[PDB]
Length: 580
DNA sequence: GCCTGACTCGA
DNA sequence: AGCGAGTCAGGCT
Ligand SMILES: [Mg+2]
Image (cartoon, rainbow, N blue to C red; front, side):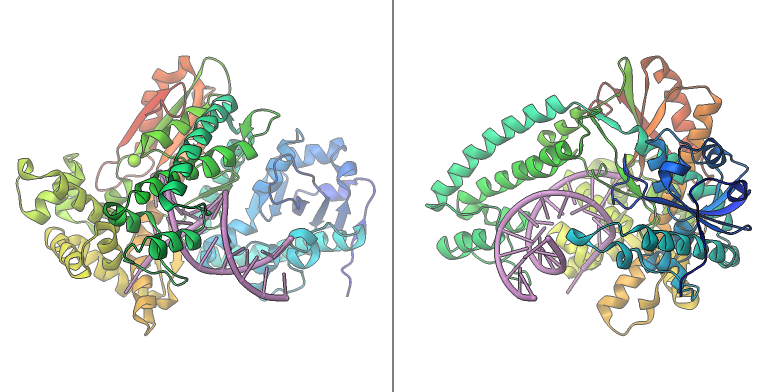
């Protein structure tokens, strides 16, 4: 049963109504400088398909797209906005984004096309994109009749689904979360992606040359120590050398076979000289393949920039993710890897990189939501939280805290921030499960409010079916009742952790919105480039650094008011590396 | 060519 | 017996 629509070959007035569902279709996964294959508009007047070479060369249509007062409902409006930015056209007036709506209503559904969103309200008069475009090698744009019908069906679904999504959002007290937070952030993210980050490719390449030379030396050493050649990158072949030829002890197994993970190899190093060489090889080879060759592959030779895509609709927490490239895991802990960040430079001469990061935002949120007196006091005094945690769990004074005590308290703190289990903690600290449970018990005696929060939030998840964040983001936890221990225990941890990590996410998202408004109010040229969970990275003219030193931390600090202060550290320099 | 497992990087 | 992302090897259709 085909859906009625006009396959127009000129733009008409009735296509430019002030409320419409709009589809601006970009089929390439990476939408930067990507083709727009077709356009559909559904409004009070009717349903329309337009060919993009017609529509996007039409002054009236382009004006309509750019007119804030002409309201549009879309799915994944950031994809469309960015593709249009590459063509010199602004998209404004997007007042409803179905992707973001579906994501807020239930992030566990994994909604990534109109059809998956529509199915949530029993609407099935639209096909999945995968059924129309194909997948992998077979992926293709079909002939115009099939394409046009698909785009009009997606637009009609958007038109029909706006009301029931907005109604459920409102029942959930999430309507302002959509309208005041996620949608405005989606525009800000679109600008960041489009701007991109400049890369000194010449420095990356010379780095790669040194690494290649280093890898070759260590690789030869390994063959000599093994007395043969083999694929060092294959955990199977490496397993045969280590555990069969060299008869090293098997300390841990993986579902497939013998574990060759870094932590197992650390413990084998005293038996054989090969082990340290393998570890060195794995460190260098990760830098080379993931961070030098991987970045070079996605730099546009055209501008020497990388344009990441932020997935705002993926995580259970509310966190953002970053792809092509992933700019959220650039090395920093070890000096050799950290030098990679010397390759990320300002895009204009006499500009600098500015970076501002929250200090312990997750634990500060926990203090706030648990109202734990001791944790709150510690933050109100701006104490070193790991030293203070050590003093309390070991019952020592400050000057009796040894480096090992601090490291282990830091690990407990880490476990709380990321919701890891007693098994996780034990793995992390290389201790027994029993000792790890002892650590946790000690922590709860020092922080009874945290313990009480942890009990209460698990009960609330059981009673309501879900937990919520500070700004009303929601996670459903149906596994909370399960009779499988490991399935149930995971859900309980997610009940504990999601209000911590998801509230941190909420705050930094609001800070991004507040900051973009302030930058414009202050007439600064400073621009946001990246977000990395608890940190914001900007670039600006050197003449703006002193003002940004005062402005950026203040905006981030004041994004919300909690029972404890928020605290923001900042740095700036010639490269991302130097903004430390 | 497509999928999966093993490994490792960040916050 | 955390999460996402990317790389690599090795296995099947
Ligand atoms: Mg920090």
